[PDB]
Image (tube, rainbow, N blue to C red; front, side, top):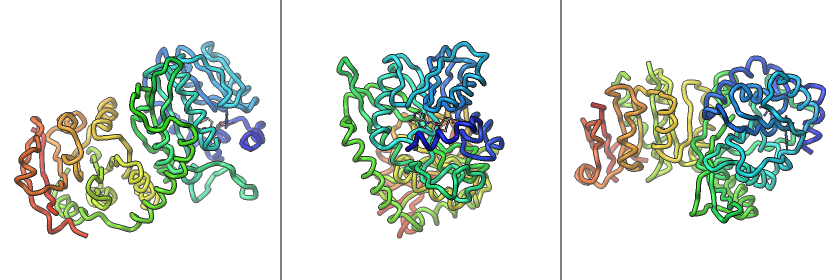
Length: 431
Ligand SMILES: Nc1ncnc2c1ncn2[C@@H]1O[C@H](CSCC[C@H](N)C(=O)O)[C@@H](O)[C@H]1O
């Protein structure tokens, strides 16, 4: 049982236990800062911290929040929580299972969790997510962070508090399973309106990339938004979907493992000629083929620059996280976003800038408005290289809209190089 697994740490109510890591003091302040800085401004918010343990995130929320409900099902973690946070007067405490937490409906601006769904069975996962829908105001936020595929301490097990003599009951699910669950969930309120989670992004916690070489500490930020259309509303269908999504992912690995991108020869060649201080932005949606993508690890090895790469298909995003763990190149990080605009939205809010773009199907896959918005996250006169499928140069040139703030300086037939159909290398620059 998960309660007895955690209750046995009752006398170790400390940071090591919260991260199940004997070296947590090398990680905790950086992990906390990574998570906090990706959250919305929670000044004046009603926050709910579920599975809070001793309350390390509650300590930070209390500085600015209107109110924090801080909850956990281990009584002595809440006792240490109250002791550590005794100076604050804006925190109420509940010893409760996440599922039995009492929160008023439409009362909460942020439901915050960090390592929780991995301690719930599939049925409990779904029921809990539906509880957060009920607690959240419209436009409210849900934060989820989970250990995907393997424990946070990774294969080395260095510093892990998991006993080698006892089984570990934790569920280490695929990041693509949680992502689809959040994407497809639907909930109907007491007045008959249906809602969904707008999943703003999926990201790896950088502290664990940098210090643990673990890209599979994945977290998500979601907004509760109206949804007349549906994904899956039935709880039992949602439960079954989680198993189907795992199977589909296993077949994606079987298909993709060890296959190099058909675009790799062209990209290596031109990028070997170009000089791009800033990270590079990589975008790979894989619209026409699962085998046409940007090899970010080759970009980083050749340019020496850090790379932020976006995959918009949850299955391919998860596969590239696998590749990151295998390559162990800290310069490369992957993210998931619904589309280009979602990525621009996030990075623009951070006022981040990228030194150039290397993409496949950037024009094939994206609206005119989003391509026009891309300048918001790019350095001045940044250059964009994208491999585009087309019927012909004339087909492409007709009915492609060049954003007013850039110009295409080359549309080169590279069809003979993108092979196991017409492929164009489009070279553009910001004006
Ligand atoms: N079903 C459940 N309901 C409430 N708390 C739970 C729970 N399952 C696990 N927990 C608690 O969730 C915590 C996971 S360890 C993570 C603690 C905290 N979120 C942090 O990041 O620092 C533990 O404190 C454990 O006791």
